[PDB]
Image (tube, rainbow over all chains, first blue to last red; front, side):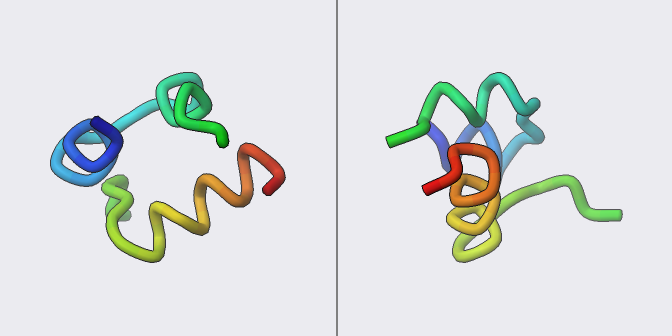
Length: 21
Length: 20
């Protein structure tokens, strides 16, 4: 999920945007 | 530059890009 993708690894804007709301 | 986003930095990034 979002912590694995953006915290453990590095995520792009469009990955991050998939978690909006 | 740290490109990882954790904890409240991750929440602030979401607030920024999602606008809420």
